[PDB]
Image (cartoon, rainbow over all chains, first blue to last red; front, side, top):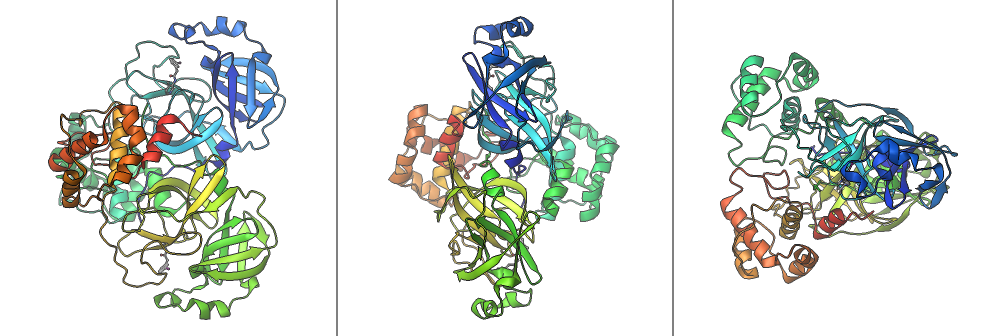
Length: 304
Length: 304
Ligand SMILES: Cc1ccncc1NC(=O)Cc1cccc(I)c1
Ligand SMILES: Cc1ccncc1NC(=O)Cc1cccc(I)c1
């Protein structure tokens, strides 16, 4: 019973958080095995940030300039290298709390949990989605850079995001753990406007299936539609076009509820065209798009 | 930048989760020091649940009937006792992962994080509020009983909730860690309807302050009100009456934003009377009441 915006248990990630200081800048690092991963802008001063030449800035840095602290103990830095927009600090000690892990570059529409950190210490955990415009709508303040996004499959943590910056519009941009930004964003204090933040249609349908499973059914109607007819409505409302891959991914939810994907699309079509009329769905007065079909199945089945 | 429904990092609690089995029932336990805490209905069969006599059922149970497993290793049970609606299983080993902790009985309107577990394994973490009718709107399936609610102050975990049951209305009831239910609920499969779920007014105002801090200001108006005038509106909309204690608790948010509490009440009054007119606040189309004034300050300052 019930449906919540649920994050993964953060323990395995908390054991990887460290504090990295270079000069006067302190941010978060991720310690996995004998490597600490952190945003390369840790080497920048506020003045450098307008147009930084990271290769030139990094020349003036030695291993001893990178202060890495895990809890209250200091890690010895024996190597440093820049991989895209991340720094990799080789330390002399493997993290004893290193979980089984992978680095994954997620697709827009996919969700993940963020462990927001400051000075290497966890402050909280929440669930995010990579927006179709490659931004994330997070909760981060100065000092949160280096906080990571991740998913967990039983005992394996798949790291997918590392926080780097806030855009002037209050949305967030970052990289995968290879240091490549999601989207066109660059790690410099410059005019970087975000593209259209469209709604993740397959996720809204998954959340509608979750609502039916949990008893909220008022929005079910007597109608059906086609992918092409639905997509005309989706375009008008800045929803992502629905494909047969999306319909296929909703198959288990359609099978569990007995509601054909195209019938659910027709409920969504009427919801887009007529609104909620002051009503709610799973305690929300808008269509929620940050639950994937996998999230709905996981939460509705209790995968640990 | 940004505002999210954030849970505490769950690591300290994950290290306390164990599986408790008695006969054919398996649920979650909380292992702190040499004691495992779990819902006493672990001793019940589905038939017992209609009208169980826990004292009589517990007579037929010995220490060896309580199977306690921490990960893949078995704990030896050397004692058992019933305290209200919880069982306390004394084990021969102190939990080496026991964090600094307290047991607290929270007040309605207060928030906490839940680590949903199944078979002693964490599935996810989310933020809840104890509703004014003493229910929680969680996400729990069969096997989740014994999952706990908690708050964290730096290194101290204050446990406040232990999940016991789902009401026929899909809302959740449970106990504090002394086994006393929140509200009038009893641990038996019987007609237990919930009272009026009123809105936590002080929390909605705190969330309105969070919105102003984060840039969402469209709802600020040219009006003010009084506590008595505001409370006439609050009664009409099933909002909790606002007191001077609530105004005092909003003091830091009022000081940070420069918006007097009664002016914010007048914005809330107009929002209640006229609705959002298709607009959103912090990505929500309804007034959010599961952020306390302390939560807003914590999130907006980055307390770790
Ligand atoms: C202040 C804040 C809030 C949330 N998340 C991150 C930050 N920090 C920054 O963005 C600092 C910064 C400034 C300009 C460019 C770059 I690269 C980094
Ligand atoms: C099925 C479920 C879903 C969510 N949270 C908890 C549960 N489990 C129960 O409530 C089992 C139960 C039944 C009747 C009385 C009692 I005491 C306990």
